[PDB]
Length: 85
Length: 52
Image 1: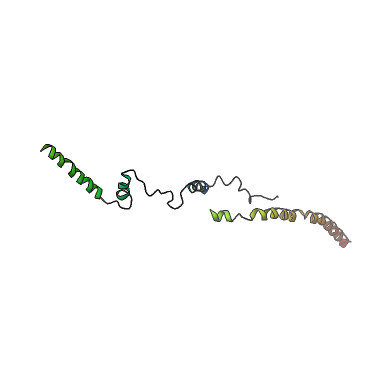
Image 2: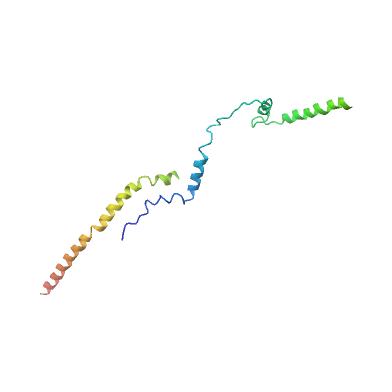
């Protein structure tokens, strides 16, 4: 008998629907992320950070410092051999 | 979600014309209702004068 009006009721609609939560989630997820690996600070030196940079990053990751640390125990007690026996 | 956004882009601009022109085409025919009164009285007159 009259004009019905659901073309323009998106005003208080855009809270209730389910991907609104994902939309408001990832507009918050996307702003403070650094763009392209920026602010990396790829070099730092504290007399042993170079040891981590050469040995303990994701790139090198080989067991050799263990080997070095193995030799460290080989370096340790054998000298104590020369202190004891 | 970009698609469901983009469907409703120019729609309110068109339904503020839909509304007006549709209700005008609804309610400019009570003219034809008061025309129908003039129709049916003349039809009754034609019926009784045919009986004459």
